[PDB]
Structure formats: structure tokens, C-alpha cells
Image (cartoon, rainbow, N blue to C red):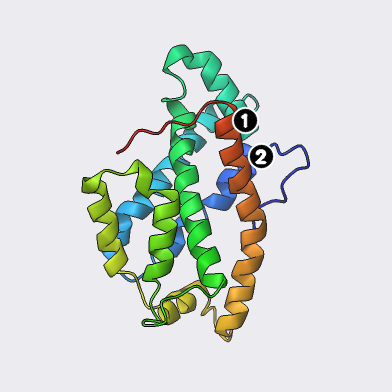
Amino acid sequence: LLRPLPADKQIETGPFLEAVSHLPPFFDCLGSPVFTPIKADISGNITKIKAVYDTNPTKFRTLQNILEVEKEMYGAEWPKVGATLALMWLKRGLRFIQVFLQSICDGERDENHPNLIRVNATKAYEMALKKYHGWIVQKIFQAALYAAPYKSDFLKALSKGQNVTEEECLEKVRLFLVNYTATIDVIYEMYTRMNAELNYKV
């Protein structure tokens, strides 16, 4: 579980990185090397932010501090720089996971293929990432789509710490999603507020 959102909405950088660093392992249980480009990217961005944070944990105590400090540091180059840029991309990967898990938890599915998760992944992709990807990168994500595991296999990979029903697994995901969604929401709101959001395509 992520930390509760402080009432002032200031996300502590350390505990944030700690929490999100638990996410990339879940990719390794999707049953294909076709997810390693996606995992490497999310892990890559967590590593970049931690790197900046570790240089001055006090100065970078909160995510907002990162943006404020780097803006001061890099001037006109900001926000296309440093941990700000890493977190701009990270939040999109985190949002993908959020939408994807929420979609599954909400019972959204293709009635023709109730044991696939392609509709959930496509939805998450369209909502979180697609607008920032050119066709080269989109092909990489479509490959991940057709390699996506069966829903039953995925939910076993989330649980199967053993003796947990699929409904109980979904209950635990629903709980995780509460603070996770709020955190991601606040990060997006901050990027917009601070004019840190860039819309270039990769």
C-alpha cells in the first residue's frame, strides 16, 4: 500500500519511490519477455528520480520540491530535465497501471473473451500513454497487448501466495487502488499546476 495522502497533498519522495519500486516485479509475472521494455522504462524512471533525490534528500523531500528545485536549477530548460522529466513519464506508467487495475476490478471485459485482459490494457493504454507515443513505440505496446496473459493467469500472478480466491485478490487490488489513485491524481494535478507537463511524442 502507498502512504495515505497528506492533507496538504505533499508527496514525500523517499516513501513514494519505496512504494512504486514494488511495482516493476509484478511485470516479471506476466509470462513474456515482451514486457521487459515496459518494465525497464518504469524502473529506469524510478532510478532517475532516486538518483536526484539521493544527492540531497532534504532539498528533494517532496515531489513538489523536486519540481521547484529543478526549475530553479535548470532555468529555461526545465521541465525537460532531470527527475522532473523522469517523473513526468513515470506518472504516465503509474496511471496506466491504475487504469488497467481499476478496469479489471470494475469487471470491465470483452464478453467474447472474458478470460483475456486486452480490453483493460487497451483502455489503460489509450487513457494514459497512447497520446505520447508515435507509431514506432505504439507497435511495441501492441506486441505487449497480444502477449498479455490470461486474466486467470494474471490474477494468479498477483496472488497465488496461495489460497486466495479471484474475488479476494480483486478486493486486495481495490484496496491498493485507493491511495495509489489519489497519489497519481495529485502528481498529475501538480504537473499541470506547475506547468511541468510536456506533450511531445516519443
- Say which quarter of the image contains residue 118: bottom left
How packed mark 2 is, by other alpha carbons closer than 10 Å (few <14, some 14-19, many 20 or more), is: many
Image position of 13 with respect to 172: above or below: above
Residue 26 location (% of width, % of height): 45, 64
Q: Residue at x 56, y 26 (%)?
A: 67
Q: CA distance from mark 1 to mark 2?
A: 7 Å
Residue 139 location (% of width, % of height): 23, 54
- Tell whether 134 sits left or right of 16: left
Image position of 144 with respect to 59: above or below: below
- Mark 2 — residue? 11
SS of the residue at dot 1? helix
- Say which quarter of the image contains residue 53: top right
Q: Amino acid at mark 2?
A: Ile
Image quarter of the C terminus: top left
Q: Which of 34 and 61 lies nearest the eye of the viewer?
A: 34
The reply to whether callout 1 and callout 2 are in contact (CB within 8 Å) is yes
- Mark 1 — residue? 64
Q: Amino acid at mark 1?
A: Gln
